[PDB]
Image (cartoon, rainbow over all chains, first blue to last red; front, side, top):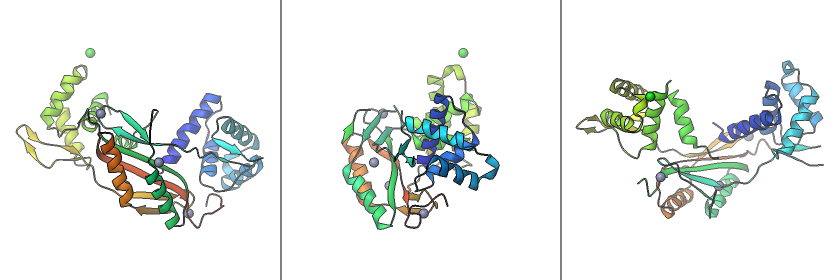
Length: 141
Length: 149
Ligand SMILES: [Cl-]
Ligand SMILES: [Zn+2]
Ligand SMILES: [Zn+2]
Ligand SMILES: [Zn+2]
Ligand SMILES: [Zn+2]
């Protein structure tokens, strides 16, 4: 499965709940619609796309408006202005000891460059990634 | 580079979700994942007995669990000890994947330079590397500047 999405969803559900907006089916469609697309939305266009694709949601423009606002304040979305898209914050990678749970955070520039080469080579624009290494530390063996 | 640092262990999260009961069933799976050893049903019992007496997992629950966590695939049983079969979590090698977040197109890959770098990173920090996960996310050449397809 797409791990990036599950992390985005968890984080979305958390922002809603913390901000005291309900987590509903309408909001989940809304997050999916922003994740799976490559274009920027106004509240008006995001509402139309959702209304058009899932008519039985009875999505209203106010939920869309208020969610976008909550997401912007949480830095989950960026705004070009109106016009929004999910933020892609750069991040590091992790190595996890299977025994004691010690974690090493790292970023290896040679690996980062190869990932961009793999993407270029198959015509992908590279947008995100996840890397974890699992092992046993020196102390645990 | 290395950095001072809440992170989820994805291969574990997945293992647990595949396993899907009780607090006893959980401690067993956790014991197998967190140990750098091959257990017999007996050694596994004694280990949970040393560490979680209060939960009293019977030897029957141990055999039953291992059997069930076997006629699935989740554990491998190759080799013997005096006390019985030795068991290991299945740890198959795998390739890496790039996924288009629009059309779901999946490209499988394995780049030897990255795999050797991962070996170096483990070595530099004194770790023995036993597994890894690498997913790349992006927009394939067919999904540029488009909505959910
Ligand atoms: Cl007790
Ligand atoms: Zn990375
Ligand atoms: Zn350790
Ligand atoms: Zn790999
Ligand atoms: Zn695509």
